[PDB]
Each structure stands twice: as C-alpha cells, then as structure tokens.
Length: 305
Length: 301
Ligand SMILES: Cn1cc(-c2cc(-c3cc(Cl)c(F)c(OCc4ccccc4Cl)c3)c(=O)n(-c3cccnc3)c2)c(=O)[nH]c1=O
Image 1 (tube, protein in one colour):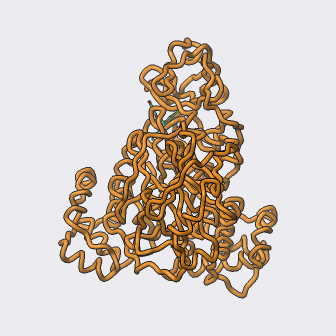
Image 2 (cartoon, chains in turn blue, green):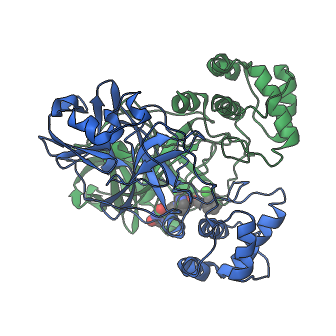
C-alpha cells in the first residue's frame, strides 16, 4: 500500500555524467561510448548569448577549448560536432559504464526522471512530467545545464531530455538528446514565455484510480458523463481534452477497480465544479497530474528493472 | 529555481541489492563486504507469524537453507548470526560494488530516500521522512521487505532504514541496520497501532523559508509570537512541539531571509487558522513537512 512520486533507479545514468568546461562556463555532459553530449550554449559568453551565431562561434573553437572531466580523470577531446542545439565532443575513451540506451523524444503529458547534476556530479533524482506547454517544472540551480531526463524499460535507458535553460517564470526548457527543443523556445538570452499551461486530464484520472486502489473512495458516485460533456467541462477549467485513446489506455485500471472511465470522469467533473470539500486524495489537496496510467500500473504492481 | 522532493541518486545502493530465499519466503537483502543483511522474518513459516521464536527457528537452520542470489550469481552462505531483528548472512564473496557506508539511527522528522526493491531488483526511488509516530508513509508491496532507506553525503551512504512490514492502516515500519525497530513495533502479526501521526513543525517552517527564498511572500504577516504561545496554538492542529533546539536550527534560514523564526511562527499560526484560500505554496495546497532545514539549504543553495 501507499503511493509516492517515484523516480527510476538512476544508477545506469549516474555512470555517464561528466563535467564539461569551455572558457569560464562549466556544465554537465552525458558520456556514452566515445561521445560527450552537452548544450551547445556552453561555447557562448554572456555577450554571445544575446544573439549567438553558433556555427561561427564553433568554427572559432578547437578541441582544446573543451575541458572534459570524468570524476578525477581528464578526457581528451579529439573532435567536436554540433547536432541541432546539442554539442557532441568526441573523446579518446569509450565510457566503460555505458548502458544499453537509446535516444527517444517524448510527448507532452509523459513522465520521466531527471538526474540533477552539478559539475558532473549527480546530486538528486526526481520524477516529473513534460507539461502540455512543453516546459518542465523542475528544480535546477546554476550549473545544472546538461542534466538529463530518462525512462528505463527492462535494462534499457531511454534518454528523452537534456536541460538547457530556466524561463523567467521559473519553469525549465530543454531538448531531446538529438538537440531538438521541446516547445517554442530558443537557446538565446532573450525574453521568452511559455504558453498557458493546462492539466493533463488522462494523468489525473490515472491518479484517481491509484487512489481507489489504495482505499481512497469518497469521490466516487453513481453517475456517468459523456466524452463530449466532460470535454466541455475540461475546456472550461483548462484541462487537456480526453480522447478515445486515453480512455482505452485507462482500460486496465477500469477493469481492475470496476470504475469505468466515464464514471471516473463524472467524479472528476464533480471535483472540478465543486472542489474537494475540504478533503484530500492520496495526501494531496490538489488533483495530481504527473502520473501516467502506466506509472500507476507499474507502481501498484511492483515492476522492476 | 523550483522546489521538488528530490531523492538521492540510487546507484550506490542498487549495487548492494540481492535476493534472499529461505523455504518459500523471498525478500531483499543488503550486500555489504561479505555480509548480507535482511529482515529475520525471512526464516518464518505461516505457522510462525503470531509468536515466532526466532532464536529457535534460526538454530535449526544450516547455511545451505539460505539461497542468496546477486543478479544471476548465487552466493554461498558460510555462516549466519542474528542481531536484534536483522539477520546477517556471511557469504564467501565480498561485494565489489560496496560503497563507503555507515549505519545511522535517525530521529523522527529526518528525511531519507527509499530504493524500493522486489526479488533483489530495484523498482523505484523516492524521498520520505520518519513520522513522529516512528512509521514512514512509504510505497511498498509484498516482497519489498529488506528494501533500505539511506542518505548520501559526499560519497558515503548512510543506511538508516530497512523495511520490515506494513501495518494494518497502510503505513510502514522497519529497523535501523542494527535491527532495532523504530518505534514500539515488533516483528510478529499481533495488534499494534501506531500513535497519532503529527505534523513535523520544524520542517514546515523550513519549507516556508524555502518559499520566501523562491520569491513567495503572500503568507507573511505583521505579527510575532512567543515560543510558548505558538506551541499552545500549533498543538491544537496536531503539530509537534517546536523546541528551542528547532529555533536554533532555523537560525541560518532566518538570517538568509531576514525573517525572525518567531515571526515565521506567526505566519504559520495564521496559515493554520485561515488555510490557503485557493492559493498554493511551492506548488502544494497543503503545508509540507517532509523537507528538513538541512534539505532546504541543500536544494536552494
Ligand atoms: C512470506 N512473506 C511475507 C512478506 C511480508 C511480510 C510482512 C509482515 C511481516 C511481519 Cl514479521 C509481520 F509481523 C507482519 O505483520 C503485519 C500485521 C498484521 C496484523 C496486525 C499487525 C501487523 Cl504489524 C507483516 C509484510 O508486512 N509484508 C509487506 C506487505 C506489503 C508491504 N510491505 C510489507 C510482506 C514478504 O515480503 N515476502 C514473503 O515471502
């Protein structure tokens, strides 16, 4: 029993984190095989960040403009390359701790673990969701750039996120591991704002199912809504629309609990209009939306890696 | 910026987790040097649940009654001893992944990370706190016994909790790594309720300091309070008493924010009286008590 915001075991990823320095800038790198990956803005000065020409800033650099430390060992950079907003430093040594891995791009509403790092040193791990507005609500300080987000499937690490910047509202923006930004953001020191965020409806429903599985039942009722009716309510409360794929994904949870999805939508519909009436759900006074249906199934069934 | 409940990176603990089997009971063990630590109720049958005589059950076992598996490798047990409620299995191979470690007993309100495991394999990591009633509000299924709680400071893993059991109310009880239970609980299935779960006041105050650090001031007010008047009020909401020790501990956060500890106590008194009124603090709509003063300094600076 119990339900916690649970991150993947981070050991496979810890063994890949290194420190990258260029000029006065130090941030984190991801060392896989004989390549180190880091944000391309490591090559920028404070003046460069205002309007950078990355290809030109990089032509003017050599392999020895890059100091790469793996713990107490210096890694020799023998080549450098840029792929979108990510810098690729070839090194002379393969990482012997390189796990089975792949680079994947996730969809908003999907969750992953972030291994927050500083000077190549892992400091903490936390679970989060990619917001519908493509930001993540992270916890990062100066020096956390280059920290990565990931999922684990069996023994394979799926790297999905690399941290690049903090936005003026305090939320965070980054890229996949092939350097493509998530969201309408650029790696440039200019005014940028994320769009209005919304709540991940299908995740809230999954969390209500986790609540039922753990004995929290007060929000259930005898009623049912329709997808049409609910989505009109959802739109009003800045909730993501619920699709037929969402209902199918919640299928297993509906089977295990005996609460059909549109029954739960009726519960959620009532929770949105009337609130929580001074009660909590799984120790929260808010509707939690950073658990996917798959998260709920895994945590409540005890899947290992 | 931002504030999340971060756990410690789990890699150093992952390299210590093994599977321990005795009879038909299988749970997790912690493999450090040539010793595997696990809950002693691994040696129990269904007929032993109510009044197990552990000394009697153990004397009847030989080394080969214990199957220890590290990954695919079976480890040979060459000796066993019991220390309080923890079994210590001597194995013929030292764990090459053994980190720098120590065993620490923590006090209520302290936080730590849990590496939840089943069959010797990690499922996930999460952060939690020792409640004032000496339980933890974990996430644990059958087969999770032997999972451990830990902090990491520099490169030293301080193990502070080994999971033993889930109480009827859904909360969790365990021991330190010397096998002494936290709280009044025992490893048999007789009735034992946990005391009233109270709120960890010193942690709530530290988290409010974290909110001011991160730019949120809406809950402050122009009042102060005496320590005694604060405690007379807060204890009516089932908050733990705040001691002068706690006040001293909050001193650094007070100095950083310019808000006196007793002034923040005044803000907390008003928050208990008013609630949030539709607002949030650091993304929560409740007062959070699982961040210590030490944690707040750690994540904010
Ligand atoms: C055979 N067997 C047993 C276990 C196992 C044993 C226990 C467990 C162990 C001991 Cl000694 C107990 F006195 C105990 O009393 C529970 C209780 C009942 C009624 C009143 C008060 C109390 Cl306290 C429980 C357990 O609580 N859990 C568990 C389950 C869910 C989450 N967390 C922990 C699991 C196992 O994992 N593997 C395996 O093979």
